[PDB]
Image 1 (spheres, each protein chain N blue to C red):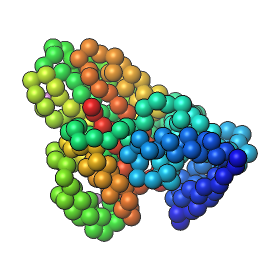
Image 2 (image 1 turned 180 degrees about the horizontal axis):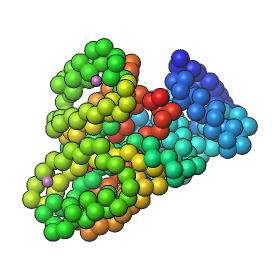
Image 3 (image 1 turned 120 degrees about the vertical axis):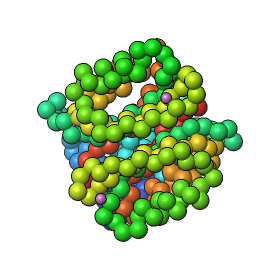
Image 4 (image 1 turned 135 degrees about the vertical axis):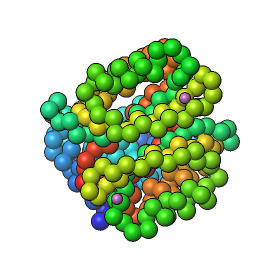
Length: 139
Length: 134
Ligand code: NI
Ligand code: NI
């Protein structure tokens, strides 16, 4: 249940990929490609069909100035308006002007990606990255 | 010239690859993977960056089979053994079988990479996706 298949490609592309792995942490080529395939297949899945589907899972990671007035509440307001469901939030108080949150979200692809974009655009948000999951990965 | 190299995919990923080939009009697994590689190579800065000794904050998102006996213990063993400083780990249940955990941690590129790969390799772990800051 862990299959091998061969990929054909011109030696120049393989080396291009190999050159790029020399400066990369990636333990191995197969591992890099496997993870690229996963990432791309998830992206493709998130790009399609129904806005009726309210069942994608994702995690939004944010670093922001929790000392800034209105900022936390603006994030809450945006999440409330998005239609997404927050399953759980973990918050670390890093210092006077930095908080890290991991926000576990469920909802449709649109609602979730829009939440990331809106939050990432706020003054005082220093970092906002979404981790996507697709059902083929866990069902 | 034309070379072949081998790729090892879990069955669930391979089935999705096959479905995507059909949905998007590709002619072979080789063609789709080749095109994926071209797109990746277009990007300048990959996630595994250029590793160094600087401390960074990171988040690992893990989905795993909660019904796999002793799997959580294996994850605890890895996290306690890690050279990283794990700040906290939060678990929820997604459905009857799958659980999702987030691990918030601090460490260098090498230490964070080791943690991700070790957890990702466990039977019952569906994936371990890394987010690094700085
Ligand atoms: Ni805080
Ligand atoms: Ni349980």
